[PDB]
Length: 76
Image (cartoon, rainbow, N blue to C red; front, side):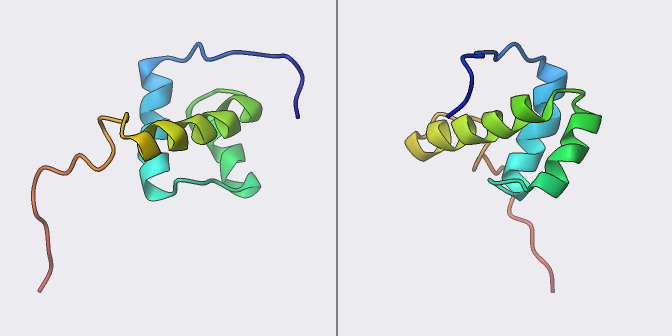
């Protein structure tokens, strides 16, 4: 449970840095979040929660940037 603070006012720029994270790790730790608040400039509580909601949409298939590969990379 958490206080009644509802806020999702984010900027494409800030979110951009997140979208990249979610992909690398659908879930972030307390040691990683601290960093996100330095690249996105958004409160830890604002980022932590974000990741949660992100999972929902994805599971349903809302995200348009996720699993949106374009090319087929590889290595010999």
